[PDB]
Image 1 (cartoon, helix red, strand yellow):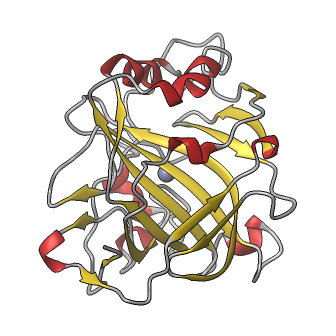
Image 2 (spheres, rainbow, N blue to C red; image 1 turned 90 degrees about the vertical axis):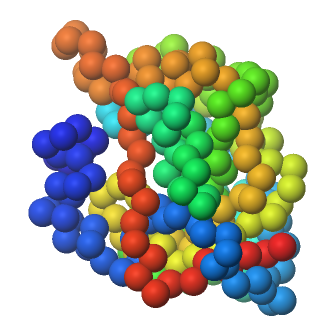
Length: 257
Ligand SMILES: [Zn+2]
């Protein structure tokens, strides 16, 4: 289809998805001596309802926890946005080693994994589908995940994986508010950017938390144990799903702090 291995991986993605070499692609390296600070950034506010949590899904290169997105029970407001973005899923990226699984890098420094929390613009559009391709369509929080001490807040997700082992497998994941995964500081960078895997739409306003969160080495291993294959085939562990940082192409990262 597209994937993360040598032959279908990130460096080949422009072949089929030629936007991969676009000007607003993601991740980036945040150079901190080149961010512009902003008066106008409001503080980020997240208000999620745990009863909108719905299902954990293994999609072969990763997994995702979907939320119910029929209404503004779980929203993202503030920061750079004038209207409310509606939560629809959270997922993680990770790498082959502890030394680099993150997507965003800060001043060249790579973290072990990255949490993406994704919201769509339900003041402007009527579906994720309509919003997903729009410049103002998507809102995504990125949390860098630093290997270190086990992170207790991962437990429910980590314990649910044992039931979505194979590509396609899915399962109810309920009563979870994923604002418990964010760092306690809400400092962030924002830049105009993209989906980090294919379709690669340039539709994401990114929110990179300044502060990292923890993940232990063994909890990363749990992510890597997930299988990219369908039950009954050869086991193919999900070693990694992180995209190299892209060129800023004249964009500016704004600091909130
Ligand atoms: Zn992602």
